[PDB]
Every structure is written in C-alpha cells, then in structure tokens.
Image (cartoon, coloured by chain):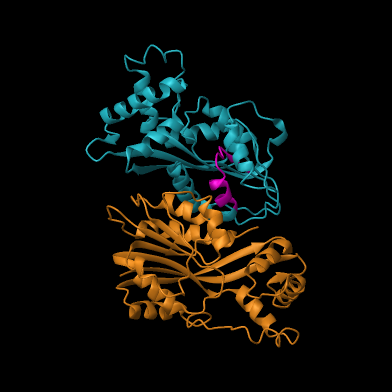
Chain colours: A orange, B cyan
Amino acid sequence: NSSSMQRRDALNSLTEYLPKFKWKESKEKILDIGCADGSVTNIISSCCPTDFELFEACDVNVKSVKYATEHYGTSKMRFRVMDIESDLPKEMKGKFDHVFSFYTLHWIENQEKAFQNIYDLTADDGECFLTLLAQMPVFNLFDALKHTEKWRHWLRYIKNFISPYYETSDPDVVIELLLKRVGFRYVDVRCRQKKFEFYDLKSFRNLLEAVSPFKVGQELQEELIDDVMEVAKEMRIIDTQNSTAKLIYNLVVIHCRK
Amino acid sequence: NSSSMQRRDALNSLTEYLPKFKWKESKEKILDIGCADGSVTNIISSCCPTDFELFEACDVNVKSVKYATEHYGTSKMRFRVMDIESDLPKEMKGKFDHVFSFYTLHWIENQEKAFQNIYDLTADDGECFLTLLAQMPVFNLFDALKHTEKWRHWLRYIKNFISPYYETSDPDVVIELLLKRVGFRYVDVRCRQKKFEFYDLKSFRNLLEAVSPFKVGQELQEELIDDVMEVAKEMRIIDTQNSTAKLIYNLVVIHCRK
C-alpha cells in the first residue's frame, strides 16, 4: 500500500515552488485537482501561508477514496467528487485563486479540455501549479501487454488515446505553446527526470494492481498482472537478479498565471 | 485543530536537506524522535529514497496520540512510547542509521542528555537531522503569565528550567560546540527565521490550549488561557485591531554525523 512516488513528487515540487508564487489575497479559494487520499491536501494547506479561512475545495473521480478522506480530511475545508475531463460546472468557473493538479498515474484522454478547465476554474491574476508525466514506463508496460499476441485480440476494443506532449521531444515547449493558446498570460514549464525504486516485486505488483487500465474479472486479474510483471522483466523495468524494480520517468512542472 | 507550523516546518527543512545526506545503506533502520501524529512520519518514509524494508521506529511521550497513529500509521513500520530525556533503553543503542527530531513545542529540561541519547541511538557513519527552537514567543508568553502578580504565587513550585542555547546570542555555535563535545564528527547547524500567522484568535487559543505547560483544573483552564490571550495582546503577539496573531520565531537546523 504505497502511493509514495506521487506523494514524494507532489511534496518536492510543492516545496521547491512555494517561494515562487504570490498569494497577496485577503480571502482565498484554493482547488486541488486529483486529490485521492488527503495526505497531499493536508500538507498543501499547512504549507500554504495564506488565509483561505474556508473553501479549500478538492475533487477525484473514484468516489470511495474521496468519501474515505471526507471522513479523515475533516470539515471547514470542502471535499467533492469531480472529473476535469467532464463539462465544467459553471458554478465554480473563475472561483479559485490557486489550482493544484499533481499527476494522477491514470492515462488522461483529453488534455486541452483539462487545461481549458484549469483556465476556466481560475480567477484573474490567479496561479496554477500542475505536474504531469512526459515519460512513464508504467504506461509503456500496459501498452505492450495490450499488444501481446495473447491479449492483443481481447483488449483491441479498449481505447489507447493520445497525449500531444507524452513521449514527444521538448514536451515542455509543446505544453507551453498549448497553455498560452488557452489564454494563460504567464507560463513556466520545466522537465524533471525522477527515479523511484521498489526493493521487492510485491510492492511493484501492488502499484500495477492499483493502476491497471484493464477491467479483467477477479478470476483473470491475477493472470493479467502476472503477464504485466513478465513483460516488465522483458522491458528490464524489473531487475530479475535483484528482484527489484526501478522506474525512470520524466515529470513536467507547470507554473502559470492568467 | 492545527499543528500546521510544526508540520509546515518539518516539511520545508526535510525537503531542503534531503539531497545533502547519503543513505549508501543496503538495509537501514530509521528512528523519528517526537513523532506525535504520523503525518510527518508518513511523508518522511515516502521522501526517504532508501530500503528500510522494516524497523522505521518512532516515539512520543503522550501515549494517546502514539496509539492513535499505531491505528493509522499502520504495520511493518514500528511505533513506540518513549522519552529521550529518560535513561536510554540499551536495546536500541547504535541501532539507527538515520535519526529525525523535529521540534516539539514543549519546553525540554535537559538538552545534552537528549543530544547524548541522539549520539548513543546512532550507528557509525550514521546521520542526525534535528530541528529545535532558539526563540519562540509561545514560551515567553507562558513565562510572563508565570510572573503575573495574579498567578506568580500559585505557579512558583513549577520548574522553568534553562536551555544553554535558547534566547542566547549565536545559539548555532553553542549547539555546534555541545554536539562535537558529545562526540559528533561532522556537524552543520544553521539559524532559520520563521513566521506563522493565525487569522482568527480561536485558532491561536487552540494552540495555547494544546501547548499550555500548566495543569489548571478543567474549572480554571478557561480562566488561565483567557489571561494568556490577554498577556499575548500586551506582548503584541496578538494584533487586537485585526484579531490576528503572528509568531516570529527562530529555528535551529542541525545536520550532523558520527
């Protein structure tokens, strides 16, 4: 049960960039896109040196984890279920002075919609701090499995989708070009190479079981992840001699203002 | 219910210094002095890029909060009740490759004992990352109340104690001199000026109620903290016109090796 790399990365990126944004607000309404567990939300709020006396809003699509935090993240700092790929509830358009979107580790289908939503959810002279993934071997892992002669036929009807910036050259400029066109006045995108090591394959298997894009039966789910773990060895994502797994991935840190 | 300044400070100091220490260990046993809520312990573990497959040990003196986290911080990463001012359980002498001690906000009676314990709890070529408080108006606040003609007589038998480094000039050199004498081969002590603002007096009162060094009856505890809040206005720790409270305090960041 480790979501640690998301938590570690959310943390290091937040701390590194805290000094770079200006709050200069008497009241303040802050939104956190892809909250999941409130572990990050709870440290964000404490690390934010501003008033935000109420309406620290946060959303996720998985509604079990959201409610699980509604019980734990506590009151007088709102929780919600929401998708940023869905059409915007106009009620909260331009409601938030600060938006946080740390990477989800679920493949996103439509980016510019999500970016346009981040643009529409932000008030004026309001800041956005987003991180997302340019290269992530976990995505490459499942994609390969989707293309094994065993599974290729049965997962054909599942949509791979496309990121206009994922595993492209200079994803930082691509995303900068996109965000300006969406209307963002200030933007500052940087690539950060990250490494996360799993010291037992059981920990690695639990991530893949959490992240699997595939809806196999309780019957098959074992067999599926067994074959992903095998593909992971072929890919050298797993060290077969150490029984370790190292993820080398590229993080895109977006700091922008409207 | 905000322990945020301890959490915010633990965080910023940890992240800033993560790149500066070398793990270079195959196994690893890590101890966290003054754990309280496992909020910091849970982010430390995720931010530590090392094996520590088991024996991530942690202690506090208040046994309700410890058990409260034993239920929440989960298994295969040990919890314990312990005081670092008490005589060392030899069982864990030189057991830990990394020791963390983020400041407690309770006045410590004996430092060199605690420092000597930090020295005895650490294995060889093992790192210590400690933060503690050089100047903190909260301590000055209660001290003044201890010396009001109303309370002076009734709190006379309570011990004020002394820090050889607290509200001294160059506390950084004093603590460096002490830690070397304890035996530490590498030491690197720095002063960090910190500011934390409370935007309502109710939040401030809840801290003081949590931190109060004084054992007044449920009957009197209200009257006591009412008088601390009044002393806080006299001290200009509380802005009477904004109904805010700003804490300007000095943090001592210790990075050392045996």
Q: Which quadrant of the figure contains the C terminus of chain A?
A: bottom left
Q: Where is residue A200? Give x, y as percent.
A: 72, 61
Taking the image as shown, residue B22 lies to the left or right of residue B227, namely right
* Residue situated in front as seen by the camera: A85 or B29: A85
Q: Residue at x 41, y 13 (%)?
A: B154
Is residue B3 visible to the viewer in this orientation of the structure?
yes
Is residue A197 shown in magenta?
A: no
Is residue B170 visible to the viewer in this orientation of the structure?
no
Q: Is residue B51 above or below residue B149?
A: below
Q: Where is residue B3? Give x, y as percent.
A: 46, 41
Q: Where is residue B78? Give x, y as percent.
A: 68, 43
Q: Where is residue A256? Give x, y as percent.
A: 35, 69
Q: Residue at x 38, y 34 (%)?
A: B205
Magenta part of the chain: B31-45
The image quarter containing residue B117 is top right
Q: Is residue B86 above or below residue A32?
A: above
Q: Which quadrant of the figure contains the N terminus of chain A?
A: bottom right
Taking the image as shown, residue B52 lies to the left or right of residue A21, namely right
Is residue B32 shown in magenta?
A: yes
Q: Is residue A53 above or below residue A162?
A: above
Taking the image as shown, residue A20 lies to the left or right of residue A191, namely left
Q: Residue at x 62, y 83 (%)?
A: A158
Residue occupying the far left of the picture: B241
Q: Residue at x 67, y 47 (%)?
A: B77
* Residue situated in front as seen by the camera: A77 or B194: A77
Q: How many marks?
A: 0
